[PDB]
Picture (tube, rainbow, N blue to C red):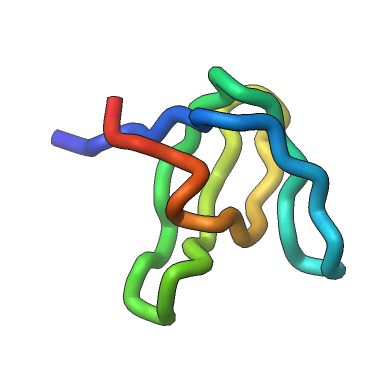
Length: 59
C-alpha cells in the first residue's frame, strides 16, 4: 500500500509553492523524484505543494 509521512516539526513556507504545516500533520507524497523538496498532499488541508523532505518521517 501507500506510505504516509508525518511532520516532525512545524514549518512556515517562504516560497510560493511550498506548504506551511504543523508537527503531526500527515501527507501523501505525490512526487519525490525531483530532489529533496517533495510534492505532497496534506491530509489536513487537502492542499498540494512542496515540503522539505527532512521535516517528515514515514508513518
